[PDB]
Length: 146
Image 1: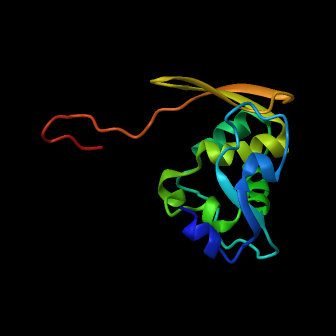
Image 2: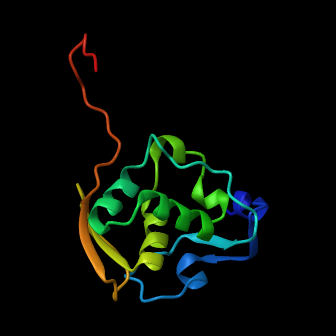
């Protein structure tokens, strides 16, 4: 289903996987998600200031400023892939990471409950490891308060 992507005024050309749009030595399945080239429209989408953990993690690992990571994303993804509706609350995904890996030459072993997944490029000059914990519910005391 590419409805939002076909209707995106910030996109141009045909729909294809990102790893086909920006070819590189990707670690399968990095970049498999569908996207379109970004045209000249400038992104309104603001920096996800309340959901920036992935940018922070990559910034700490590489010394790359978070605003630079964000600028690179805004130049290389159309708005409908940059923000599928949940960016401001759930933040970036490993789809976004694929773009950062291609531009900045990165590879990261993502550690999660069900198993590790390494994403990025086989010829990356920066390598690091990030723990991914998914959203989840936990039973707490009746009068629990943050």
